Image (cartoon, coloured by chain):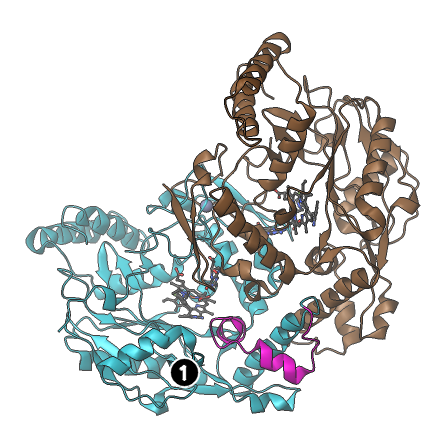
Chain colours: A cyan, B brown
Amino acid sequence: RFLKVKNWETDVVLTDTLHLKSTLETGCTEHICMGSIMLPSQHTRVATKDQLFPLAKEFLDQYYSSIKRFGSKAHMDRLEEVNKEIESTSTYQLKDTELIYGAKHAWRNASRCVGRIQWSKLQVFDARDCTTAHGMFNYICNHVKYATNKGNLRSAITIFPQRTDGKHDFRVWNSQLIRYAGYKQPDGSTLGDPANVQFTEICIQQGWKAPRGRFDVLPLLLQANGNDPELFQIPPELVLEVPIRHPKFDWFKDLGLKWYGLPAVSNMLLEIGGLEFSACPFSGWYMGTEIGVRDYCDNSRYNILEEVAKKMDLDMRKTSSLWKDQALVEINIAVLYSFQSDKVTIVDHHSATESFIKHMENEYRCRGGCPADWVWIVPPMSGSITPVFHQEMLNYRLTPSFEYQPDPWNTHVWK
Amino acid sequence: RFLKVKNWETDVVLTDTLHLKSTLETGCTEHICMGSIMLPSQHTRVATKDQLFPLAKEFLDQYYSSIKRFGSKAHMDRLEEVNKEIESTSTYQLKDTELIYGAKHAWRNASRCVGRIQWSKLQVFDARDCTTAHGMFNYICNHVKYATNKGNLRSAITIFPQRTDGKHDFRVWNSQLIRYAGYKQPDGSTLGDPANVQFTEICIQQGWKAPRGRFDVLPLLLQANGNDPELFQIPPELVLEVPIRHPKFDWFKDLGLKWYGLPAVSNMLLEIGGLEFSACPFSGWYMGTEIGVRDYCDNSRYNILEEVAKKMDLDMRKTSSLWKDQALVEINIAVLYSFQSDKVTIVDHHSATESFIKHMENEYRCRGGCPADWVWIVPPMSGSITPVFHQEMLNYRLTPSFEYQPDPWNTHVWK
Ligand code: HEM
Ligand code: HEM
Ligand SMILES: CCN(CC)CCc1cc(F)c(F)c(CCc2cc(C)cc(N)n2)c1
Ligand SMILES: CCN(CC)CCc1cc(F)c(F)c(CCc2cc(C)cc(N)n2)c1
Ligand SMILES: C[C@H](O)[C@H](O)[C@H]1CNc2nc(N)[nH]c(=O)c2N1
Ligand SMILES: C[C@H](O)[C@H](O)[C@H]1CNc2nc(N)[nH]c(=O)c2N1
Ligand SMILES: [Zn+2]
C-alpha cells in the first residue's frame, strides 16, 4: 500500500510511497512489533557471488537514475562491465563517484539519525588503497583533523578496503574514534566512562599504559587485512575538547567536566551494492542531549545527577520532587553554552528536531518518503515539546545502509 | 519464536512466550514497522454469528483455566450453554464473574498503559440493565462518586449494554467524563481547552448554555440504545478539582490554573469473547506528566510554556537556552505538589515507570510476557532518566481488549 503518516501537532499529512522500494526486513510481523528492540537480528550483517549481481544492478540502477541517465549507454555498459567483473573475481570495485553516492545514501537511509537534513553535505575519504594499520592510523588522523576544522565541524567518512573472503577484514576496534576510558576500582566503583571498561582493558591487554584518570582519551586499536590490531595514540593537539561550564552557577566549573567535540562512530558496517565495508568511521557534530542526558546522566554512564542536584540545593529525599529532572535541564543548558562559547559546532534538540521535520517534508516531496525510527528520533528529554514526538513515522530499511556488526574480539582468530 | 527482551540499564533479560497466544494484528509487516502510527486500522473496531463461538470458546477457555478448572464439567457445560445461546440468539450474555474477569484483562492487556501493575484491583460496575440516557447519567454519577472517594482515588469501570444489531448502541459522546470546554474567539485564539472546541460546540448545538470561560466542566452527552443523545450536568460537588500552586514560586498561584482529579476515558470499546461494549467508561488516577506536560504544554492544548517562562525570568530569545525545558520541569513539580498537598491521588513518572518495570517482571514470570508499547510507555519528559526508556518491549494484541471506535457524530442516523 501507499501509506499515510500524520503529524498530530499540526495535522499535516504526507504520503509514503518510498517504502515500496524497501528491500530488507524489520523484525516485525503482523502479530508482533519489535520497534523497541535495540539490535534486532536484521539491523546486523558472508555473501556469495550468485547473490551479488542483483545487488550491484539494483544499486547501479539507482545511481544512474539519479545523475539523470537511467538506461543510457553509459549505464548499460557499466552494468555489463560489473557483470563481467563479478564473473571474473566473484566481487567488484566501485567507481569513486559510485562510492560517494553510496556513502551519502547510507546516511540518507539511516532511519535512527535525526541529523540527516545534512546528508548530501558529506566529505568522503577513499582509503581503499590502505594496507597496514599504520596507514589506517594516518587516514584516521587526517579524518579527525579535517572533520574538526578548528571547531567548525564538518561531516566526513573514511572508507577502508571492502571485505573479501572474511578472514581478511579491516576493522577499527574502538566503537568511536574518540572515547574516554573506563577503569574499575579496587573496591568496585568506576572511574571515567563505565561503558568502555571492557575495551579499556583490551588496550591494557595489548600494551596500553593507562593514565588511570577520568577523561583519558583511549588509543586507537586498528586491524588491517585481518591481522592482529595495533595501538596508536591520536596526537593530543588533534583531539578538541570543551570544558563544561554554566552561564549561571559558578560552582559548575568546579564539577570539572568536559567532553570531546567530535562524534565519530567506527564500529559499523557500510553496505553499497552488496559490497561490505567493515571499517568506515564517520563523524558529524553532537546534538546536546547525547552528552548532557545520555553520556552524563545514564545510570550506567557518568551518573552525575546526584552531584549536580546536591550543589543545586535540591529536595533529594522524595522522588516526586523531580530533582532529577530539574538537574537534568541545567546540565544540558551547560553543555550547549560551553560548546557555543568555544565556537564548537553543536545543535540543541529543539533546532535538530525541527530540521528533521523540515527534512522529512523534503523527502516525501522529492523522494516519496523518509524512513524514520521514532524510538530513536525523539530526544531523551523533553520529548513532547519537540515536534518529532507528534510526528508519525514509517520505519523501513533501504540500501545503501549502515549496519551493526559483531565486535572484533569475539570473532577474530588471534595469536 | 520464543523471543527475548533486554533491559540495557541493568542487563536483565526476560523471555516472552505469551505472544504465541496473540491473536489480533499490529499493522506492522516484515518490511515496515508502524509502531509510531497513533490510530492504526487494527487498534480500531460489525460481527456475525459464525465468527462468534470461536471467540466465546477462546475466552471461556481462558476464564476457566484461571479459576483452576480448565476442562472440568462446569467448563464444558458453560461451553455448550453458550453454544446453544449463540445458536438461538446469534449472541450471548456473560456471567457477572466472566464480565469482571474480562474487564480486568482488557486493562491487563492494554499495551499502551503504564499503570497496569494495578490491573487486578478494578471495581466493575454492571450497567447492562440500563435502558435510558437518564439511567446512564445516574450510573455515571455513581461511578464518578465511587472512583473519586474524597481524593483517595479508586480504579473503576462501568459497562453499559453490549452492541446488538449496530443501530442500537449505547455511547458516551464525551471522550472523557470530566473535560474542560474549548471556545474559539471572535479574533481567532482559543479559551479553555483547544482539544475540545469541536465537542464544546456540539453541546452548544444540542442546547448547552456555555459559561464561556477557562475551566468549564462540559456536560455529559449520553446516547442510549441508539437514540439521540441528551445533555446532563455532573453535580459540581462530584467534580473534584485541584488548584495548581508551586512549593517555591508564589507567582505560580496567580497563573490561576487547576485540573480535575479523575481521569476517566469514555469513548473506547471493550471487547470480551467477541462481545462489543460500545460504552464502558473507565477511570484511574493521573500520572503527573499527563497534566503538566501534555495538557498544559502541548502547542495545540493550553500552551503555557510562554507565560511560565516569562514569570520565571528566562532567556526566551534563543532556542538553545532550554527555557522551554526549564519551565516544563517547574510546571510538573507544581502539578505533583498541588495534588499531594490536597490528598488527591497522583503518581510521578519516576514512581510509575518503576512500578511498570516491576509489573513487567511479574508478568513474564506468572504469565510468559507483558505486551507493551514503548512509544506510549516512555513518559513525555525526561525519558531516559526513567527505567522504561532502557527496557526493550514486545508489542502484541491480546483479548479481552480496549479498542478505539469512530466518534458517534460521524456515524449516527440523526433527527
Ligand atoms: C551532521 C550532524 C549529525 C547529527 C547532529 C547526528 C545526530 C544523530 C543522533 C542524535 C543519533 C542517535 C545516536 C544515539 O542516540 O546514540 C544519530 C544516529 C545515527 N547517525 Fe546521525 N548525526 C549526524 C551525522 C551523521 C553522519 C555524518 C552519519 C554517517 C555518515 C550518521 C549516521 C548515523 C547512524 C548510522 C546512526 C544510528 C545507527 C543505528 O542505530 O542504526 N550521522 N545521529
Ligand atoms: C490506575 C491508575 C492508572 C494510571 C496511573 C494510568 C496511566 C496511563 C497513562 C499515562 C496512559 C497514557 C495515556 C495518554 O498518554 O494519553 C494510559 C493509557 C491507557 N490506559 Fe491506563 N492508567 C491507569 C488506569 C487505567 C484503567 C483503570 C484502565 C482500564 C480499565 C486503563 C486503560 C488504559 C488504556 C486502554 C490506555 C491506552 C489506550 C490506547 O491508546 O490504546 N488505565 N494509562
Ligand atoms: C551500540 C549502540 N549505541 C549505544 C547503545 C550506540 C550506537 C550509535 C550508532 C551511531 F551510528 C551513532 F551515530 C551513535 C551516536 C554518535 C554520533 C555519531 C555521529 C556521526 C553524529 C552524532 N551526532 N552522534 C551511536
Ligand atoms: C484520542 C487518543 N488520545 C489523544 C490523542 C487519548 C486516548 C487515551 C486513551 C486512554 F485509554 C487513556 F487512558 C488516555 C489517558 C487518560 C487516562 C485514563 C485513565 C483511566 C488513567 C490515566 N492515568 N489516564 C488517553
Ligand atoms: C530499549 C530501547 O530500545 C533503547 O533504550 C533505545 C531507545 N531509544 C534510543 N534512542 C537513541 N537516540 N539512542 C539510544 O541509545 C536509544 N536507546
Ligand atoms: C506520533 C506519535 O505516535 C504520537 O505523538 C504519540 C506518541 N506517544 C504517545 N504516548 C502517550 N502516552 N500519549 C500520547 O498521546 C502519545 N502520542
Ligand atoms: Zn513494529
Q: Quadrant of the N terminus of chain A?
A: top left
Question: In the rendered image of this protein, does residue A239 appear above or below residue A388?
Answer: below
In the rendered image, residue A81, in percent from the top left (x then y), is placed at 13, 53
In this view of the protein, can residue B86 be seen by the observer?
A: yes
Q: Amino acid at mark 1?
A: Gln
Q: Position of residue A119 (x, y in %)?
A: 41, 64
* Position of residue A264 in the picture relative to residue B28 (left or right): left
Label 1 crowd (10 A; few <14 / some 14-19 / many >=20): few
- Taking the image as shown, residue A77 lies to the left or right of residue B178, namely left
Q: Which residues are magenta?
A: A290-318
SS of the residue at dot 1?
Answer: loop
Give how far across and how far down residue B54 sits, in percent: 51, 20
| Magenta-colored stretch includes residue A93 | no
- Locate residue A283: give its quadrant: bottom left
Looking at the image, which is closer to me, B133 or B77? B77
* Residue of label 1: A185
Say which chain tag 1 marks: A
**Residue A296 magenta:** yes
> Depth check: A235 or A324 in front?
A324
Give the left or right position of residue A59, taking residue B389 as reference: left
In the image, residue B27 above or below residue A87: above
Q: Residue at x 53, y 49 (%)?
A: B362
